[PDB]
View (cartoon, rainbow, N blue to C red):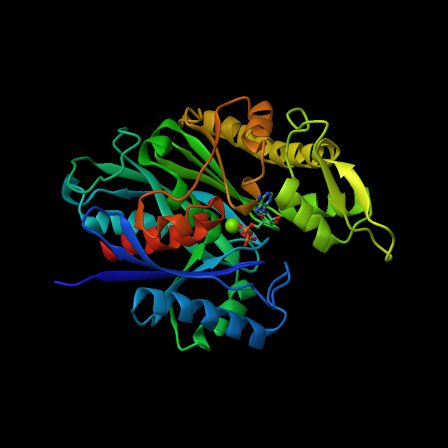
Length: 388
Ligand SMILES: Nc1ncnc2c1ncn2[C@@H]1O[C@H](COP(=O)(O)OP(=O)(O)O)[C@@H](O)[C@H]1O
Ligand SMILES: [Mg+2]
C-alpha cells in the first residue's frame, strides 16, 4: 500500500550527508531526499566539538527530511577510522539429522564469531563467506542440503569500542535512533559493485580524505578488509609543502586542477596560486602540479597492491579463489581526480575503473558522484536489512 523508507547518514571529514530512499519491488532505491552540510567539528582523529556536529547532523537531516516530505526518526550510521581491522575464522558442526536446517547454520556461525578479538575491539560485522558440506566447498545458501559435517568460513570486521560513541551521541542528540553502525568501506562496495564482479573477483578501494578502505571479494565472498590511514589529505599536504601555499589553497588547486598523471597534462595550462606569509602570488604549470600528485598517488595504490598480493598468496595456500578477474574499483571522494584510473592501471597491472553508486533512481543527479559511495551504500545495506 505504501513505501518502505531507509535513511543513511555519513558524518565525514568535510561533508555530512543524509540520504532518504524508498525501497522498490525491483530492489532499486528511489532516492527522494538529499541533505548536505559542511562537516563542522570533526578532525581526522574524530569528533572534537559535539555541539557543532549536532547542528551539522540536524541541518543535513532537516534538508533531506523536507526534500522527501517525510519524517526521519532512525538512521543507518556510517563509521570510518584508523582502528578498523578484520579477521577470518572457520567453524564446523555436525549436520543435524544429516539435513542442513537453520539451527545448523546459526551455531556454526556462532562458533566462528565466538573467538578472541583484537585488543580493545568489538565485532562490528559478522559476514559469512561460504559453506562446505562434506567436501562440497564454496556453498552460499546451504539450508536444506544433505551431508554429515558442515564447515563455515566467516569474515569478521572489528572496530575499537569507543570510536563510535561520539557520533552515536551526536545522532541520538537529534532525536534519532541508530538502526545499525555500518563500516564505510563495506557500504561503499554495496554501492559500486555488481554481483558478478564479486564472483569474478574484485577489490574495492574507498579513497576518502584520511583513510583508504580496501575490500577484496573473491568467489562472491568478502575475503579481506584493510584500512590504510593515508589518502587525499596526504596528497594535499604535498601540494602545500612543495609549492609553499596554504593547505586551504592546496586543497582548492587539487580538486580544481589536480591530476594523477603528469604524462597527459599539457605544458601550456598554467594555474595561479596564493602564497604564504602574505607574499606575492605565484604561477605554476598544471603539469608541474600533476608531477607532485603522481608520486604520492602511485605510492598509495602500491600500499593497496602490496595488500592485495600478500592476501592472494595466503588464499592460494588455502585452496580458495584469488584471481581478480573483475579488476580494481576505485571509489570515494579521493578517486575523482583526473588520470587516476590510468595511474592505477600501471600499479595493479589489471583493469581499473572509477565506480559510482549503482542501483538507484529518482534524484540520481545529486548522488552520482563517487564520493557518495558510502552514503548510497547505507541505503542498500538497510534495504537488505529489511528484506530478511
Ligand atoms: N575532483 C577531485 N579531485 C581530487 N580530489 C578530490 C576531488 N574531489 C574530492 N577530492 C578529495 O576527496 C577527499 C574527500 O572524500 P570523502 O569521501 O568526502 O572523504 P571521507 O570519506 O573521509 O568523508 C578529500 O581529501 C578531497 O581532497
Ligand atoms: Mg568517502
